[PDB]
Length: 335
Image (cartoon, rainbow, N blue to C red; front, side, top):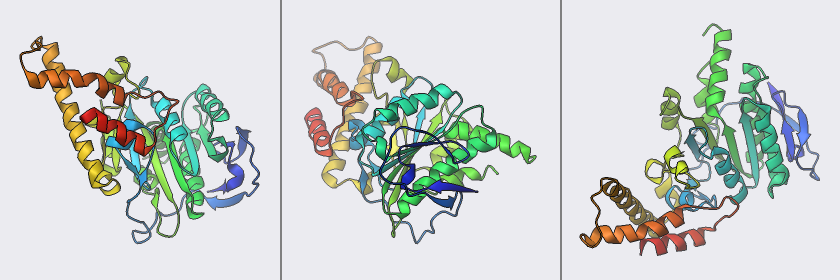
């Protein structure tokens, strides 16, 4: 019912009991405090409207799927779609004050994988990791998500710009289904957990990224899609083509997009999406064997744009782009 919070947790790995079990970085601060893991979400009059972009350093997200401070964003992917590599890029190339990672997983190898990534990350002294493996009970698996959220909420009240990562909502929902059965069934826990992020008028912000594993979409993908403020789809087909990040721009959205980017930006993003739509249309004509050079000048122009459009979309995972670099690059692609 209560957990450790404070700057003393920076660099620490926290298990479903709230105890520090490992450290991936050591910090000056020793402030440790105690707060309850669940408390009510901010009243509607305490939330601020989402108005400021949360820059990720990822070209396709920052230009076409621009996130906002306080926004809750879903990441939908099947296994083997680079879900973990995208989250590592989000941590590495964004500009949050503090990163809180909650791993609701099965195998301990995944926890060590993240601890090893954090151990060599430039953001390591601003991160807290909460984990729960398969050996832990369903109750402990759920509490890992509440501990991570409460840790992020303390940093929000201190005024920090916080990024929260829950991986995954799917395995969290499974454990919540088991905890229900123990009561004879409490699923109401999902919206309650997901309304806690946001920007407070009197404090900082929690920008939250929730992972959802796809089979095709579970009812769990459909519900979760409707409460969040946007979703990124990781296309297994685009992954097999060698495109990383495997983000399907045309199937992804950020519902706060028009409120967090200016008018010049919105014009370039709309022109780029129309270019993507023409390219995927041209791809089908090519697969049909109906494209033949020199016959349709419109198709030839689209065809000659494919290489630099693909170049704009792809991104080395160790590289991050400023907002000015991204808008400059997308300008060249649409000319």
